[PDB]
Amino acid sequence: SFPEVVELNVGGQVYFTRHSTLISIPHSLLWKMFSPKANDLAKDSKGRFFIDRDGFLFRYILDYLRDRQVVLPDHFPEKGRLKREAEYFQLPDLVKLLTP
């Protein structure tokens, strides 16, 4: 079973969050990966769960999961890349919020 506080390595960037935050959006990729019905998920050299995506963009994914909204730094030049990340994580609402 997963621990209360999950430690994630996303593309090299380390994030900590509650397990409930990872199953926050029903039917999303993280919902499947972290729903208790673990040993399928890859791990880095220090035993952290590894997510093979851009670690810098994930910071906004996580904020969505926390707040159902995202504030982007001013003049953010990668709205489209973050949109693709949302598509990969199967977060439809976020995909719509980032639609140009």
Image: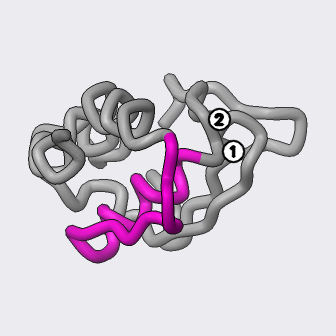
Q: Nearer the viewer, residue 4 or 86?
A: 86
At x 48%, y 37%, the residue is 38
In the rendered structure, are the residues bearing label 2 and label 1 in contact, judged by CB atoms less than 8 Å apart? yes
Mark 2 surroundings: few (<14), some (14-19) or many (≥20) residues within 10 A: some
Q: Quadrant of residue 83?
A: top left
Nearest the eye: 98 or 45: 98
Find numbered disc 1 in the image and state the secondary structure of the residue it sits on.
Answer: strand
Residue 37: where, in percent of width, then height?
24, 40
Secondary structure under the numbered disc 2 in the rendered image: strand
The percent position of residue 48, horizontal first and vertical second, equals: 72, 45
Q: Position of residue 94 (x, y in %)?
A: 20, 50
Magenta span covers which residues? Answer: 57-77
Residue picked out by circle 2? 50
Res 9 label: 1
Residue at horizontal 89 percent and vertical 34 percent from the top:
45
Question: Is residue 32 rendered to the left or right of residue 62?
Answer: left
Residue 82 vs residue 7, the one in the foreground: 82
Compare marks 2 and 1 and give the one earlier in the sequence.
1
Residue sitting at x 49%, y 58%: 75
